[PDB]
Amino acid sequence: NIKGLTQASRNANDGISIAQTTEGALNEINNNLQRVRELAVQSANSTNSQSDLDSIQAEITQRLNEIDRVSGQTQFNGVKVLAQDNTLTIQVGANDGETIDIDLKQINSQTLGLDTLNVQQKYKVSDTAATVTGYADTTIALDNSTFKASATGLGGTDQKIDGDLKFDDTTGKYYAKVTVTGGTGKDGYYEVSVDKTNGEVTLAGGATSPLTGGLPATATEDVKNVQVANADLTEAKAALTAAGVTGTASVVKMSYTDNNGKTIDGGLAVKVGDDYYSATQNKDGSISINTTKYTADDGTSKTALNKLGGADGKTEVVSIGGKTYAASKAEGHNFKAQPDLAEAAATTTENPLQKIDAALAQVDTLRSDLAAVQNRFNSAITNLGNTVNNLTSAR
């Protein structure tokens, strides 16, 4: 029978295929590393502005991310050839233990030691107060039942509010159309006091007669709920408390100054102590701290707040566990299915060209090793072929 020897040859060709697959992937990782090296040589041109460095860093980050994708996705018959350290044993002979081994290695940004390769420089960070304006409505529904017992001093038979309360975002005062049944000259506009907790509505200031001139011209909003000033940073403040943040919060406008004295404006931020949390101002004028949304850590869905830090002082970072990653990386990430990781780059990498060449050398010996194993498989295939040919041409 020849079929057992041809199966071994078949296995041997799979061994070549998996080595060639790994080799094509490493040639790609190598290209990405050479580009990263060009960028590193470019970044060392001191005439570069910080904005130039940020741009070069973005492309270095793209290159490193691609390397990580290649490492994670490259496969042969499902075998993720560069996602983990593993020795693959391939039966190329007729009997037990007669195999050729392919030592596969996990090759990625981290194992290559370039996971925090950074060429950026810190900007001088500063801010200026940005006064938040307008109001937003809460969950507190305006309870009007309590009005008629607070307006007994108007008299008559019955005092009832006609319709919805009119709010005034210029003063924060609420007003009411009031029909006083039985009264003489008591119908008109009244200012009402609103319980900012449960929403109760009561005649304000023990008014004994309607406002002179009726409803103020600034009282144009018809509210069904208690208004809260966007300046109280209701949600932002609750998020800061739940995060364990102690200081008083304030909304500021960020500014960043490079080494040449040039400053650009940043976005809005919620300043707390010395820390800055990137924020966004919503439709209604309210403000919310940026969050990133991620899976697990030690099991389950969670959330962290985006602070402004990183290697440049303006990168959205995030603290999970006892670490601080970039938010870009941390978004949609699973630390259960994929733990172990480097935080965000903290400073500029010392001797980056040395580090990139060491990564280029790692990739290269692996490639030389794989080419050597292909050679071993070719030798097996030849001997299997000579045996089978002899049997085929005979009997």
Image (cartoon, grey):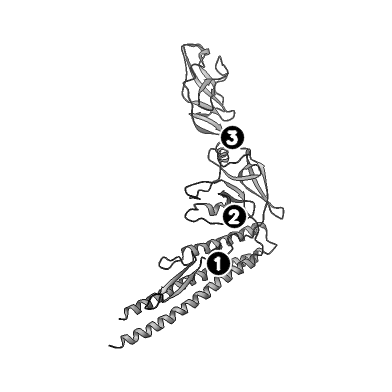
- Image coords of residue 289 (percent x, y): 56, 43
Q: Is residue 59 above or below residue 229?
A: below
- Circle 2 residue: 344
**Camera-nearest residue between 200 and 264:** 200
Q: CA distance from mark 2 to mark 1?
A: 21 Å
- Image coords of residue 84 (percent x, y): 49, 64
**Camera-nearest residue between 360 and 98:** 98
**Camera-nearest residue between 30 and 52:** 30
Residue drawn 52% across the image and 46% down it: 303
Among the 4 quarters of the image, the one containing residue 350? bottom right
Q: Is residue 316 above or below residue 218?
A: below
> What residue type is disc 1 on?
Asn
Task: Tell me whether circle 3 and circle 1 mark residues in contact (CB < 8 Å).
Answer: no
Residue drawn 69% across the image and 54% down it: 258
Q: Nearer the viewer, mark 2 or mark 1?
A: 2
- Circle 3 residue: 232
**Residue that protrudes farthest toward the left in the picture:** 395
Q: Secondary structure at mark 2?
A: loop
- Circle 1 residue: 32
Q: Nearer the viewer, mark 2 or mark 3?
A: 2
> What residue type is disc 3 on?
Asp
Residue drawn 56% across the image and 24% down it: 216
Q: Secondary structure at mark 3?
A: helix
Quadrant assignment for the N terminus: bottom left
